[PDB]
Image (cartoon, rainbow, N blue to C red):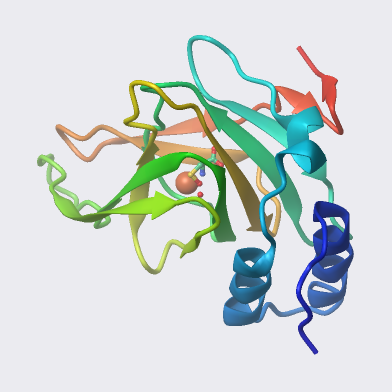
Length: 186
Ligand SMILES: N[C@@H](CSOO)C(=O)O
Ligand SMILES: [Fe+2]
């Protein structure tokens, strides 16, 4: 039974129930994520920006089953083209906008990766991706507005691949938390 999360804290309690079991109901997780109405006061503690690139800020470690984190994208900051390491990956905008570009998995041959499509994710919208859908790049293309997103990955993962748009070649990248539970972890 899916209720509206009243607060970020309420959302987190609800996610612990939804991930109590071995499987994931994606549409339900996505629906509850979308239904949370972003309230900046509730997440200011996690919203720690870096001038030069986007940051990942751990919010909740889950029940063994997922990580919840807040990413803060300065003006012009974006990701690589990457995968999600056999995990569910949910992305909800808490502030500003992000452009999401989708790519197919590259073939063996070295070859420019062409965009499958792109969309603009707006405040409070929740997107979903997994490796079976494809790869994506996420960017704050704004010149004036920082963006903040709320991401849920299950199972948790610490590593992923970045793809060279010109060749399709991939490189394993380890991901680091800029902060955990509101504490800067340098
Ligand atoms: N996967 C990237 C961000 S876009 O993922 O929805 C990351 O978590 O660093
Ligand atoms: Fe991603």
